[PDB]
Amino acid sequence: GFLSGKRILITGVASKLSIAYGIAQAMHREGAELAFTYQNEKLKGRVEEFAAALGSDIVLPCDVAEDESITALFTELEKVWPKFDGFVHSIGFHDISAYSFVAMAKACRGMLNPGSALLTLSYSLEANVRYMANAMGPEGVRVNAISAGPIRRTVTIEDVGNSAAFLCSNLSAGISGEVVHVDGGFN
Amino acid sequence: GFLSGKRILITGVASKLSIAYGIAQAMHREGAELAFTYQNEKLKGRVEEFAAALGSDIVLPCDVAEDESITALFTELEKVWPKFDGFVHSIGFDVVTRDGFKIAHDISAYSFVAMAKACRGMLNPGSALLTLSYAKASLEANVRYMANAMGPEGVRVNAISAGPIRTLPIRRTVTIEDVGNSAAFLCSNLSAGISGEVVHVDGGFNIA
Amino acid sequence: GFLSGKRILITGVASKLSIAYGIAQAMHREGAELAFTYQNEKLKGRVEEFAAALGSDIVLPCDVAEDESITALFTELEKVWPKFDGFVHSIGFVTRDGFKIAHDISAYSFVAMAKACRGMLNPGSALLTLSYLGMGLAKASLEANVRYMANAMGPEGVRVNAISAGPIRTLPIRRTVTIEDVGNSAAFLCSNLSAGISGEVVHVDGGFNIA
Amino acid sequence: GFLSGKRILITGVASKLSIAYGIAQAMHREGAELAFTYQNEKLKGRVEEFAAALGSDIVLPCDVAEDESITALFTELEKVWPKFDGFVHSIGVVTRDGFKIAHDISAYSFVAMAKACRGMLNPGSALLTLSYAKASLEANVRYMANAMGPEGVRVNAISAGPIRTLRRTVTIEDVGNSAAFLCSNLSAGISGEVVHVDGGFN
């Protein structure tokens, strides 16, 4: 698929209903190798099962709230993926979600291949993927966000997933520093 | 490819360097059947050659400036494609502005909604229309209003705002391939969750 | 390729995105044997990896800031390449130029390295210096250092040129160069194809966008 | 070679010692398909022989001094090469001036030929002009490159020094290889530039 060759880290899988899980499924379908993080120890088993379902052995702990946890994650990740092609940051409703996104970027900055793409999930707040994209663009890294509608217009998890898959693939190479609104689907 | 099953009309091919042509190439690569329009009679031969390059025999005349030309286009098109899955609208264009009767360069905005109205009945469910863009308050919610109108009948409407496209303060150059793949995506079912949106395709920094 | 037979030393590789790295890739593709220098010890491992990717075992330290480091480089180099065919010199940066712009170190290191390896250069050798732009290092900065070097070393069979590259795509009339474009121009300017070109600064800016 | 796939028109071959001839030889060696023009009918036979030597059948008349001759050339050329990849252009106020508009300038033929073949140029095409204090070294090359860049065409010049006197001498091979390079994709990052080929320290 259009993600063949890519190694992408998915954060925010907690259940099979998670938006991040549908993104992972879409990315798997398009031939990406995936890695997953679990927030807490309770989730470790579930996430390992979901990861295995998609042929992944890389399940690492990470609390995106703590900077040391992020540094630790990327220290551990480098042992199996010395280089990778970006991550999906999906920790939902503070600049805590904004901060953790820039934190994780800084933490994995050296492990990113040229052509890498970071993606943050959104579902008076202006997301500032703009400044991240301008910073990391010169070294070949793209940064974007998906602002997803409620999962009358209903978005399917598959819809979000495919947009996410696209925005992490080379198909979307001309798109960086952008917030894509995925609300569409009236009835 | 991810456009297999789709029949997409490409407007605005005038040369192989046309942005519309690169979009057609990308869409062809992803398995879409294509149809092309020529503005000018002079262009008919060129466009037929380019169309043939992408395995298409459907080349029809259309001046988006004239409403009857649009109606005529879709009348002719229905004879080969009774139903199709959307189109790419890629056609942008001395004495002091105070002057007699003109539409006043309505084009693009108007022609986009005109073509939508004209082919409204020929669109399959899941169709997608795409318009290209390449003090300037030209940012519009034409796309927003079109998407809200046509969404209930299964049709998505989006625009690509492309940065400077390499022929082949943050300077950024795009690359036709980049524009083409975004366009292909926005006309495919991959982008089913995206309607009424203007996607900015500027990306491509330089080294420091 | 058109660089078969040549042994070329590439300085200024720090990452796969380094302009010097793209030049090395192009030169490798055209059949040159390469040697690399690392600026600092932190980079030694990276540069050795990149060098190995292009089949090179010669990775030597050089801080072009210090004269002894240059002398040391060519002392070490002569042990594996007693003779070689030139090098690529790629080191970085109102009346700002009034101020203590302690560059001109980049101009100096180029002539220093030339003096240092002068005896190891085969007839037909070519030295190349790279300049890049991402009042400001393109005013009083354009020099006949290249011209004077070429006139000095020409009689002994050595050509000297520079590439002035425009903005290099990461991958006024705005233009962008591809790393491949820079690389091939560099490869050409170090090959015998460019034998009639010495003491010259070649501007590699090209790459227009459509209207 | 590095010119495989290219179709390049060489103007200014008059003898085997012509600078344009050495350029043609170098370009042939690098796998280019060539076409040649003869200035006058006296030369037609010689140029056809030289062309044949390099496996070319396309020998057309052109006097770059006359606009009609240029238009004619590209009309004829399109019959065998409907599309091509560029050309090498190699040609060599008293106040009385019988009150005449002193034409306009000099080369001019370079920009004329560019306009005339503009439609037949593939993307990635490259035009090259040869030049061989009166610093009337202006760069019409700069303005040409800016004009034709957006449609994928590069424009450059070679300013060649004295040729092997056939001190710094240029060999015809040296000029040829620089010319070959400047018409190939190797030189894709070079447009609107005047490359000085003087080198060769006895």
Image: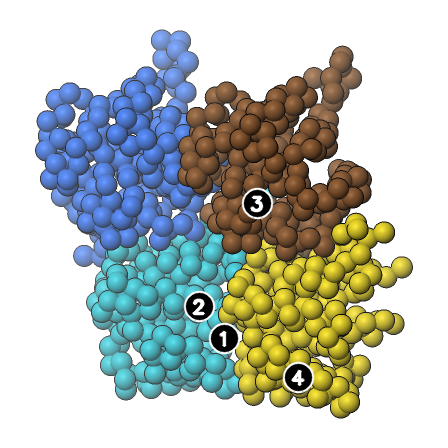
Chain colours: A yellow, B brown, C cyan, D blue
User: In the visual, does B56 lie left or right of A62?
Assistant: left
Quickly name the residue at label 3. B6
Instruction: Please report contact status of discs 2 and 1: CB closer than 8 Å, yes or no.
Output: yes
Q: Which of the chains bears the disc numbered 2?
A: C
Q: Chain of mark 1?
A: C
- For marks 2 and 4, give the CA distance: 46 Å
Q: Quadrant of the rendered structure where residue C210 is?
A: top right
Secondary structure, mark 3, is: loop
For image coordinates 56% across by 37% down, the residue present is: B10
Do pointers 1 and 3 mark residues of a single chain?
Answer: no
| Kind of residue sitting beneath label 2 | Ala
- Which residue does the numbered mark 2 point to in the structure image? C20
> Viewer-nearest of labels 1 and 3?
3
Q: Earlier in the sequence, mark 2 or mark 1?
A: 1
Foreground tag (4 vs 1):
4
**Looking at this view, is C196 or D165 the one in front?**
C196
Q: Quadrant of the C terminus of chain D?
A: bottom left
Q: CA distance from mark 3 to mark 4?
A: 37 Å
Between circles 2 and 3, the one closer to the viewer is: 3
* Residue sitting nearer the eye, A84 or B118: B118
Distance from label 2 to label 3 (Cα)?
Answer: 46 Å
Q: Is residue B14 above or below residue A99?
A: above
Residue with the most extreme bottom position: A41
Tell me which chain the residue with mark 3 is part of: B
Residue under label 1, please give it.
Answer: C14
